[PDB]
Amino acid sequence: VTFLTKNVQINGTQFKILLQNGQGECALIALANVLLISPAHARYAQEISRLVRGKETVTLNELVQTLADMGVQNPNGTDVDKQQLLQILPQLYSGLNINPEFNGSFEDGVEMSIFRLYNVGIVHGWIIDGDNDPNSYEHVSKYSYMGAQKVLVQSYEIQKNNAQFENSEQIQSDAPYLKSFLARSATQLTEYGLTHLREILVERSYAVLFRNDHFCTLYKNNGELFTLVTDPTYRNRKDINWQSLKSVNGSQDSYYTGNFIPT
Amino acid sequence: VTFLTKNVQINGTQFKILLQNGQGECALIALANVLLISPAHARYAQEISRLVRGKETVTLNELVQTLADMGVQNPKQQLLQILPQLYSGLNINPEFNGSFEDGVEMSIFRLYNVGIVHGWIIDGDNDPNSYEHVSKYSYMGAQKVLVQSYEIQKNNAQFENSEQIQSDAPYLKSFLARSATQLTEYGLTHLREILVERSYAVLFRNDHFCTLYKNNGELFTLVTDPTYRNRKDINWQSLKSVNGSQDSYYTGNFIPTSL
């Protein structure tokens, strides 16, 4: 229930974006913000633009969903989907189904299809590099985040409470490599993954990024990555619009204005 | 499985410690290093010191285990079966109130009289609603709930705790998103308040372990990265900031390396 808007300026142009409340940005908000700000989507996003225009903050989840649902019935990929989006779109606020694979894809799921419906890219950099330990790579690259968490809980249960698991050999084989990978990828972005994001995002294009159990709007400017600042802490700071994404550990990074000048 | 050793100097005393290999620091290495360097343990630590003394790197997991097992017969050779569980740390389960769930691995810590701590702690006065949902969970219990929530959404699955699962999950997700590096502002304060001056403990953070020490009221972690094997002047990293932006390396007698 309920999102503040924020007046922002990006490369000269005025916009209103949606802010997350305190608990972490959802995929639904990141998708909405891409649609709100991405020039390539301007035509398709008239209704969501108008929704937020009249609203010195405050748009509700239900309004945002009705809106997006209307938009999606008119998608232009010619998907025959009825207003059935009303059942689905709320799941993007939750995000609990959205499941990154350690090879850089996401598990195919309804949310991925929603991102396709709106022609909004969705990416992540939580990716094991096969040029590091190849023994790790073979064990881990085939897993998703949920798949991994499942194995790890299972492994703990085997020890703690005993196994009733059919694939216990596989659980016990893979759990150590999964645990080690988690330990080397604490912020759910690897060096290799960062170089992947930088490659795969086209110049002057927007996508939704999964990182740290939440989402954000990512943008590539002059070959450098930036994430949109949706933290309501900065609602009154128009000059705080972007955070650069130049390093995994954030040591080379800082806030930037709408025109990609350091704040 | 080949842990390198490193010659270090802590507060003027020479030691050899064990370094990480390709795979993040395990609780077994962190435990071993407390046994190697901590004055309180030095009478108990003869066999482990002896093991590492002339090995210029290459201490294997099996020799370390065998040794620790010999040591543990001292304030039962099921230790051999259990100690290797410390290498991957799969059953070491921090609770979001700062404890760990009790279990065989925690009993190993008590056997060796080595403290184990973490700072992945939710601050109840900051957010009482969230606290009421999250504080009661362990990491593994949270992972279970999140995996259950996924299966509820993807597969319309049925669980016994469903109202509870679905009630707590969004708070657990939120907490995880706001504590990316498994240390909170409040937990950092907690570590600093609880660790006694000149005491060592093993710290859980980011699915791995390290040796934590307190010098003059300030926290430091032992640098076990093999990239700094040839750097006797890089021994400790300060732990003053959750995001690391205030931290730096220190010599073994707590002088900034940069200086």
Image: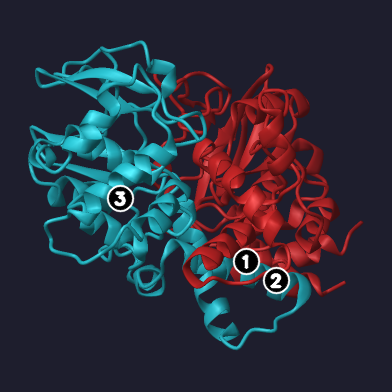
Chain colours: A cyan, B red
Q: How many marks?
A: 3
Q: Amino acid at mark 2?
A: Glu
Mark 2–mark 1 CB contact (< 8 Å)? yes
Residue B25 appears anywhere in the view: yes
Determine whether, in the image, residue A195 is placed left or right of residue B147: left
Determine whether, in the image, residue A80 is placed left or right of residue B121: left
Residue B2 appears anywhere in the view: no
Q: Quadrant of the C terminus of chain A?
A: top left
In the image, which disc is placed on residue A157?
2
Identify which residue, B15 or B227, lies in the foreground. B227
Looking at the rendered structure, the secondary structure element under dot 3 is helix
Q: Amino acid at mark 3?
A: Asp
Q: Vertical placement of A10 versus A142: above or below?
A: above
Identify which residue, B80 or A171, lies in the foreground. A171
Closer to viewer: mark 3 or mark 2: 3
Identify which residue, A167 or B256, lies in the foreground. A167
Residue B182: x, y in percent? 57, 41
In the image, which disc is placed on residue A153?
1
Residue assigned mark 3: A69
Q: Spatial distance from mark 2 to mark 1, Cα to Cα?
A: 6 Å
Q: Spatial distance from mark 1 to mark 3, Cα to Cα?
A: 37 Å
Residue A222: x, y in percent? 8, 32
